[PDB]
Image (tube, rainbow, N blue to C red; front, side):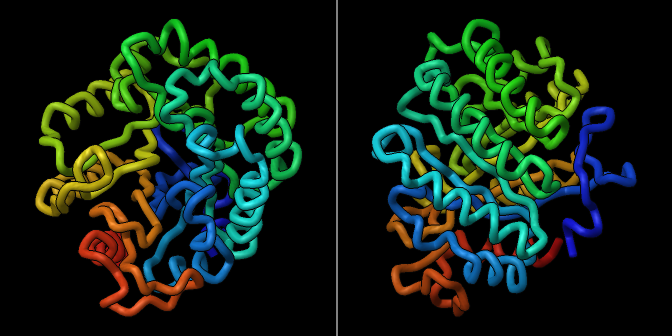
Amino acid sequence: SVVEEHGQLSISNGELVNERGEQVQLKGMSSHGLQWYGQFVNYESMKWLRDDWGINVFRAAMYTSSGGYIDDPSVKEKVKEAVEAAIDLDIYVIIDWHILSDNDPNIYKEEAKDFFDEMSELYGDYPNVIYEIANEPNGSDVTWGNQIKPYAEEVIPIIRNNDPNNIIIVGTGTWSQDVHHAADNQLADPNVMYAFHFYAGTHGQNLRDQVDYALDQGAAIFVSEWGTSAATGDGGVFLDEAQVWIDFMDERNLSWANWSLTHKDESSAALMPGANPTGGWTEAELSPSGTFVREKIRES
């Protein structure tokens, strides 16, 4: 239903729009690392998210380091499973090259080019796919102008040779918070968005003003990862601040994916220890974070 109705997404005047030019907002869940919690990524759990939570996007978080793709590339097959389920369920899917400890996206750029060539060759003629080429560039030595933008300018051509206009989300500096610098020196591709990530444990009023500054430069922003916890993914659940961000994203037509779909014992995890990896969760099998996120998507 979702993908049949909205079809080809594109960027028009800095807004995500459907194929009829109408604004569309995607709301869904991100997996945790596929090398650790890949059992929660399957057709049945994604269908349950679609039908019971109302998701219209799913994000496959393929870490590169931390025992991820570079050490064991077999995790790429779990990304393929998620994309295939999204196609079968008629929802959108984000393929996330999930850099983090490997803080400069240039570290594994050759592997990234080969991976995105493969994924775009396979899925480049489906409208469901959104490519997220560098989760969270970070470090004082990794800047938009010197490291991130040039990396994007090598990887985007690889994707575009196979898929000329599906959306590409490009990470920003300081763990995808520095949308101000990216917005002042935007990429040329017309179907790019910049990632903005937040955690509700951080007081967010200036970060909201910074997202607004970027939107004011005509940059499109996709909140491809956010949590109800502190920045570590743990340390408490901050639902008052999360609601302020939810309302902010609705007013600005910002699409988002919540972190994350796992039973890991940390506050940002959506599930409790006994949650079935194939879905069907009762109220008690959702954590306080999962209950809130589910409510937000159901309300939408």
